[PDB]
Length: 348
Ligand SMILES: [Cl-]
View 1 (cartoon, rainbow, N blue to C red):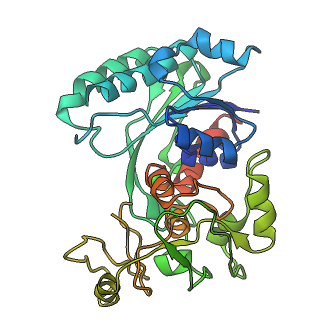
View 2: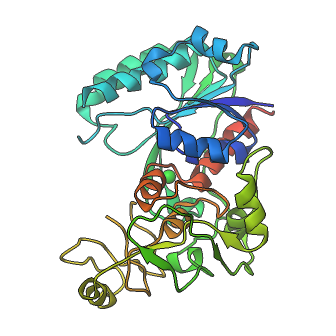
């Protein structure tokens, strides 16, 4: 048992990566009620703390556990003002304060582009300082998700540190993708219903039968590889009957529909700014993409697939919330790869 806490967890993209890599995600901390409720649905055995990280310290956190829990890793997404304001920069520093106070074997922070700007070099240096005494801090890892077999080209920075006391040697071999087959839009969307319930914002789950008669790495991750103690029981049970949630469409006017039908692959609609997916391409950074074949925006479940979430992962019922939950996540496929490198290091 190597134990992690996920700070700023959202619905648990990075958590699922950790769990699949072999870590036990013991606690998730997330301020947003919808995000953390969704995290609890998918990770019912993790502790859930709906809290501002600024109100936390090492002693408070040990108090939550009550059992002198060894915190082997602190992972998370520290917020940053980025391309946007001030409180996010405070929260950034609290992530690193917590790492310093808790002294885990490692930390992993993920950030979107915006973090490397000159105007943040002060707070990044201040954060490096809190940890550089006790940690071997790796240079930034900038990854493109599609290189790890996720169907999207979104880029992400990972910042990793490992306790000096461990005296580990870290080559990039461990984090680099090897033996990875690319997953295009067409492959990720295979077997989903062609006819879906197109509504406005309905309050009920859109459970639908899919075809699951495919083979290969992506599909094993899509329909299985459920870590121990992870997963919504009903979602898992329904998946056994080829039934999954989130297949809910949006009702479009005929004029919109005709405009979308006329889009070529990769074309951005001049009016809505939505872009039609290329079936042999990847999903751009997650306005909603237009389906490659159907004249409509994609469904939450389609977005989930394109982001690298498995079909058994359950999101909020509404399109509004689920699309935000999906867009705000690290791809679980990318997260798993990077975190498995760290797990392997800590088992030598
Ligand atoms: Cl990602």
